[PDB]
Image (cartoon, rainbow, N blue to C red):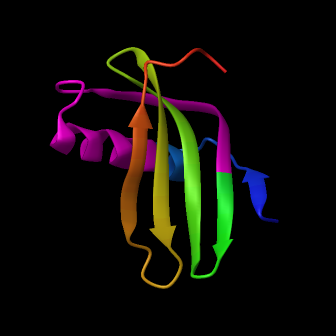
Amino acid sequence: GEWEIIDIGPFTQNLGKFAVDEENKIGQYGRLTFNKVIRPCMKKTIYEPKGYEYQLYVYASDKLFRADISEDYKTRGRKLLRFNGPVPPP
């Protein structure tokens, strides 16, 4: 469907790593150390253009953040859209 809760296994954990790595290039929160992605994790399907958006809760340097990631359907390239926090536990 258009909105879907997905698993928090390695694929999702690696999305969270990507978000923290990208956030370290902006440096808003200093040098963040990736800890863990936790539930819930949301996958939005984009039909035009084909692609996905992922909304994650990711612990980094033992703080909780919300990160939004785009992934292109055809090339699978990723972008960090949004990285906010600390946020309350879901």
Residue drawn at x 54%, y 48% is 12
Q: Residue furthest right?
A: 1
User: Is residue 71 rendered magenta in the image?
Assistant: no
Up-down relation of residue 4 to residue 88 (above or below): below
Residue 35: x, y in percent? 39, 26
The residue located at (21%, 38%) in the rendering is: 24
Segment colored magenta: 15-42
Which quadrant of the figure contains the N terminus? bottom right
Is 84 located above or below residue 82 in the figure? Answer: above
Residue at 61% x, 16% y is: 89
Q: Is residue 21 left or right of residue 59?
A: left
Frontmost residue, 14 versus 77: 77
Please give the count of numbered marks on the rendered protein.
Answer: 0
Residue 65 coordinates in the image, percent (x, y): 46, 27
Residue 80 spot, x, y in % from top left: 37, 52
- Quarter of the image where one finds residue 46: bottom right
- Along the viewing direction, whichever of 59 and 25 lies nearer the viewer: 25
Q: Quadrant of the C terminus?
A: top right
**Membership of 29 in magenta stretch:** yes
Q: Is residue 60 left or right of residue 7?
A: left
Q: Horizontally, is 72 left or right of 80 in the view?
A: right
- Indicate whether 61 appears above or below 53: above
Residue 2 versus residue 72 in the image, above or below: above
Q: Position of residue 70 (x, y in %)?
A: 47, 61
